[PDB]
Amino acid sequence: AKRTKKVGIVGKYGTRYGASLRKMVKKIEISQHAKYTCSFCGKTKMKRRAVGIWHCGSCMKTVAGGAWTYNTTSAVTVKSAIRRLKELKDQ
Amino acid sequence: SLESINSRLQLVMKSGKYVLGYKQSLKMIRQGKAKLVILANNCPALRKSEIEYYAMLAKTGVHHYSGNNIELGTACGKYYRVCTLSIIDPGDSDIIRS
Amino acid sequence: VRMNVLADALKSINNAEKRGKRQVLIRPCSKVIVRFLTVMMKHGYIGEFEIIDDHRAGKIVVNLTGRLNKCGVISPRFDVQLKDLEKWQNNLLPSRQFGFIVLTTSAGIMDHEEARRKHTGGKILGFFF
Amino acid sequence: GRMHAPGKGLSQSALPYRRSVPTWLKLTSDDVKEQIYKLAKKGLTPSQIGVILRDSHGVAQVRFVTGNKILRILKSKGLAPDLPEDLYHLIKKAVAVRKHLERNRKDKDAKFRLILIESRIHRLARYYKTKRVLPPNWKYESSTASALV
Amino acid sequence: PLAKDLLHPSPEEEKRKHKKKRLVQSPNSYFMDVKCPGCYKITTVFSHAQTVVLCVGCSTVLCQPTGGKARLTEGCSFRRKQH
RNA sequence: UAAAGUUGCUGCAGUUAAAAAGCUCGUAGUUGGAUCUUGGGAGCGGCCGUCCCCUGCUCGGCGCCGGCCCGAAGCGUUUACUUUGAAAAAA
RNA sequence: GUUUUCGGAACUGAGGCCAUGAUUAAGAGGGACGGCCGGGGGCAUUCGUAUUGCGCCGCUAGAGGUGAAAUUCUUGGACCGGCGCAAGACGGACCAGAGCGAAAGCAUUUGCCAAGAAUGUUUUCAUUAAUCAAGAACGAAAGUCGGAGGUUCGAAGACGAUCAGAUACCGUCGUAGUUCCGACCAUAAACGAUGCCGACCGGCGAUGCGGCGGCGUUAUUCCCAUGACCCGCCGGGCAGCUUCCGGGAAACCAAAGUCUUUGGGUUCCGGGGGGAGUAUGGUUGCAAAGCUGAAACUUAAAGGAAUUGACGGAAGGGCACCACC
């Protein structure tokens, strides 16, 4: 059934650490444990091994990514920057 | 012509004869049955280089699809991932003409 | 959208008469529009009229005289007895002399006097004087 | 006016009064029906055939020459697709718009359109179940729709 | 005017109206028998043709679709069907 | 209670006097185009005004000789509507 | 006693038979297709001067700001002139009673992405529609939360003026904010103080978009189709002017009309002024606050539109040594 109303995974901390830190930390604690679709094989199997390390359960392929999320916003934009700069420099 | 190959696939899935998957497709290349081999863009580089070499041997066409194995799956109207697909009878599709 | 065809037909000839026009087009024809206009025509309120049968709901050209003051639909169609019929013509007609209440019934569509002489009430369509 | 727009445009077709076949077309029921079966196996909707026939061949109406209408002629020979083509096209559009949203998150006009498109699919699917074209089992899911595009 | 005869309108009025707003609605379209000197069979083409129309044996492309009536390739003659 | 058309079904208001949701979607609710036996006959009232019709296969006769039809009854798309009758304590 | 005959009940195999069966294609709606069109939306890119800041060079006594000053910067070179450089906002004039969008709203170039109206159509399905409690998406500005950024402007704050005081108006500084990203809140004179869909009822000239037809001018010259003008037509749209249509308390409104000659369908919502969007319950939000929301008690008016007069530190035109020069 619906076990908790508003607290999700952060129910494991109970009445500790203050509402607003426990509201804040739920946004990171979902994504760091979420399973992502592997770009290489397509299987929804990418898991976080350590800090900024991501492993496919099927492909046996390790990716250096963001600490909590697989793709950081700052690392998507920079790959689009380095591509455009490679194009608009070497021409 | 990305929009059109998704409609040609729809017309060969309904009316045509073919095999999805890798080993099944590589059998039909050696049988001389395959006319066209469609590969997903995320296909392993060695499986792409083996299919291509079997195809230039058999004197067949290779299409490099503009989408990964999931998109090829939903293109074929299936609910799983298709990396390699090979058409034997185009059926009533103009896929092998383009 | 168009949910009452008498309403539009009757108020399309009503504006045309106030404006002082001699004839009027009214786009969607019916059984009940033609059976209403025939009742209006035989009491000398309109002249003769023509139907334009295209292969849809045909159009009607009515030749208007300047005799009709107002024709008015009653929507919805209140099912009236002969005892209910008396009070319906005290709040719809300006005299006990002229003007009729057109009401559909199992005999056919007719004015309140012919429904009285045939002892068979039904549902009210509209009035005219 | 329109269903999901404030537009009130009066732009449809205007069929002629003469329901007879003109004295220039020499085609007959067993000529054009065979031609419809050639264009239907090519993977065309009844609309695409109905255009092609009045363009290249001069078929004013397929209903006026032959006995029956085009989708009826395809249904009478086991050539008609499963779910109606006016429902296939709205699924195809909802799939295309939902694919635009998952790539571009902040597009709140595209999101508003997807609500109107998917609302119109539900209205057509609701109608077709009452006339018993689709099974009552049938329902539009936004996850499983790319397959049955 | 007041006494405008709506039953017998002037033919200079029914041409000057929308196709739906006439007394009896009529199409402002026609089928036309089109020749080109490349081909030999004259073909029944629609006025608002809506797609590119071809001959037998690739003589040339007859018409080309626009916002209204189709445009015919330079030197393609047409005659209107009179029935 | 009427006057109260100042609670409105008959029968009110909503630019400025009191008042239309900030916008659109949408389920109940409410409401939904046209289309299907129409004319004409037929005898008798006085050119017109009523009756009857585009229906069928247990039981009596005006009967004839496995039968030629009219008289009573089991029957014939469903409902709303109207019309009449039943049945409805007096006070 | 049996095949019976044959009364009833169900099952099974053929060929004939009816004129053998599906109304129409709405100035309803959805859907397709065609060439278009638009400051409609999203992502990226690209440009423009200006403002402030820095460095260098020039010549110099003030510059700034005001009703008049002062705070403030300056012989340590301020303001001004010239070369650069840096970062962050913004999108001038063109820009209109023009366009698009559901509303909020939207304007530098180019590309990519998905969408939409109108138009045209002898295309398609055949009533699939209209309005909608509950419910859902979007919702300016301000404001709240986490990250990046900060030059202009600038709540609060500090001072200088003014002043009878001026914790205001004026001026010099300025923090949050103003900018970008990811969540929040859900209101505005969110206005046309005007629900939506449909029907009918006067002209006139423009305007935008699409289509159609027609003297000629003009470019592509090498003529046609097309681009730019000219004269009409049709449809949809933002609007004008004009009528004793008709209505309205008038102001005014081609709708605010077709209404005691009262009935096309339907949602919301008002009941004299206050107390009061208050108290209290419930619910939503991190908060600020939102939505639903009385009563006791008080009061003869509060109010809308128009008229005339008076009045103005309102405008235009005159005048007077009981006014000035």
Image: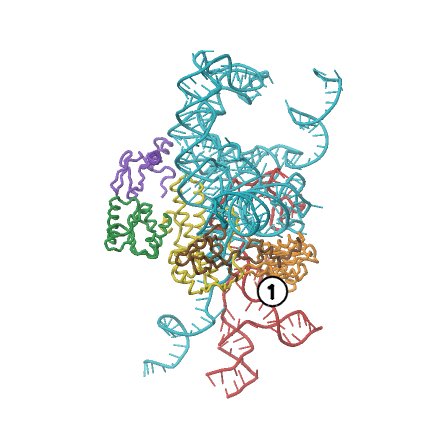
Chain colours: A purple, B green, C orange, D yellow, E brown, F red, G cyan
The image shows residue G223, relative to residue F67, as above or below, that is above
Chain letter of mark 1 equals C
Left or right: residue D80 versus residue A35 is: right
Rendering coords of residue G120 (x, y %): 51, 52
Locate the N terminus of chain A by quadrant: top left
* Most foreground residue, E47 or D115: E47
How crowded pointer 1 is (Cα within 10 Å; few <14, some 14-19, many 20+) is rated as few
Query: What residue sits right under mark 1 in the picture?
Result: C107
Rendering coords of residue A79 (x, y %): 33, 35
Total labels: the figure holds: 1
The image shows residue F24, relative to residue G141, as above or below, that is below
Does the image show residue A3?
A: yes
Element under disc 1: loop
Left or right: residue C121 versus residue D49 is: right
> The residue under label 1 is which amino acid type?
Ala
Does the image show residue D125?
A: no
* Most foreground residue, E72 or G138: E72
Rendering coords of residue G167 (x, y %): 53, 20
The part of the image, by quadrant, that contains residue A65 is: top left
